[PDB]
Amino acid sequence: KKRKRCGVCVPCKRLINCGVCSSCRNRKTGHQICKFRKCEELKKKP
DNA sequence: GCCAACGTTGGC
DNA sequence: GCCAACGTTGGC
Ligand SMILES: [Zn+2]
Ligand SMILES: [Zn+2]
């Protein structure tokens, strides 16, 4: 299964894709959420 | 069936 | 070990 966003971090609370980060500009091919909405808990840990 | 957006990997 | 690209799938 896909992990669910946490719904409580600042990114999760943002409503709208910014439209200008690289995730947003390449959305059709890269299929990624806006860098500013990406759930903090879903990022890669080193 | 659509589509937002997470998971995986070839090629580097 | 990274990440562009794609496939996938849960929720609608
Ligand atoms: Zn953005
Ligand atoms: Zn979150």
Image (cartoon, coloured by chain):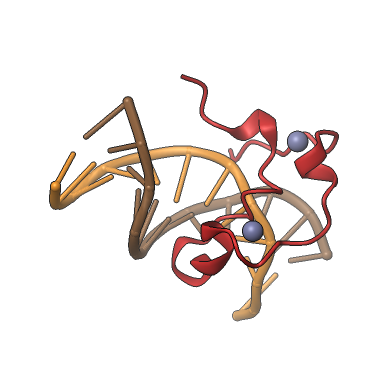
Chain colours: A red, B orange, C brown
Left or right: residue A11 versus residue A30 is right
Position above or below: A45 against A15: above
- Give the camera-side residue of B10 and A28: A28
| The image quadrant in which ligand 1 is located | bottom right
* Residue A12 picture location, percent across and down: 79, 43
* Residue A30 picture location, percent across and down: 46, 61
Q: Residue at x 85, y 45 (%)?
A: A13
Position above or below: A13 against A42: below
Left or right: residue A5 versus residue A35 is right
Q: Residue furthest front?
A: A20
Q: Quadrant of residue A34?
A: bottom right
Quarter of the picture holding the N terminus of chain A: top right
Q: Residue at x 62, y 55 (%)?
A: A33
Q: Quadrant of residue A40?
A: top right
Q: Residue furthest top?
A: A46
- Give the camera-side residue of A42 and A2: A42
- Give the camera-side residue of A36 and A29: A36
Position above or below: A14 against C5: above
Q: Residue at x 68, y 48 (%)?
A: A36
* Residue C2 picture location, percent across and down: 36, 36
* Residue A45 picture location, percent across and down: 52, 22
